Length: 232
Ligand SMILES: CC(C)c1cccc2c(-c3ccc(CNC(=N)N)c(F)c3)c(C(=O)O)[nH]c12
Ligand SMILES: [Zn+2]
Ligand SMILES: [Zn+2]
Image (cartoon, rainbow, N blue to C red; front, side, top):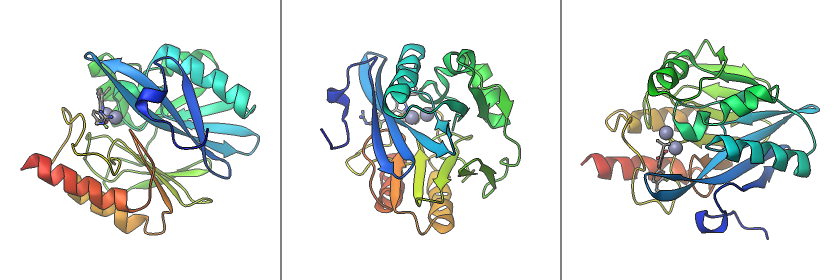
């Protein structure tokens, strides 16, 4: 009924949308992994009379539910999707998207890592993102590679029309105590990568983490803090 939806409010298999700004939504779903339930976010950006999707809803059935929820609440076709790193909360559901006619994209690094992990593999490679600080335009967003953080391949997404920064899993929510799932992370480089994001997007008004509640620019410094406390 208005506030941002939390993990215990979304049964596994249902998807919520949340209006972030004009023409910008987040999508929220929940999934089981190793016997615990987690929420996760993605993004939807209006692209004329089409939509750009950022990240799957963490699984095939969740992603089918996402497409149905978009049709119900927005009613414009999803034509392209970008996955922001190789984990299943970002690519699980790419096969559903591809069979629904959505063109799926990721960096070559993400595609290689997804293939090696046994995860679903986006079809198209996004060049121009291999060096930290690189940025490319993709429809109504800018894609930015900040350097290694949560994963070596993680991308962030900026919506310039709305000053919305989608940090993905390189950014944690303010209530977070922990650095999340760090299995593939670079804890030493992560603060430097966050500093790059801070320098590149100083006018961000909304910052969306990969998991949990959006906030403002403070999510960036908070993330650096939680990662440094973890590494130590
Ligand atoms: C590898 C991938 C598919 C995956 C599986 C299971 C958990 C995670 C997490 C995670 C783990 C705990 C928290 C703490 N917050 C809570 N609500 N439990 C959090 F935010 C994310 C991340 C992440 O870190 O990207 N990724 C995950
Ligand atoms: Zn991840
Ligand atoms: Zn994640």
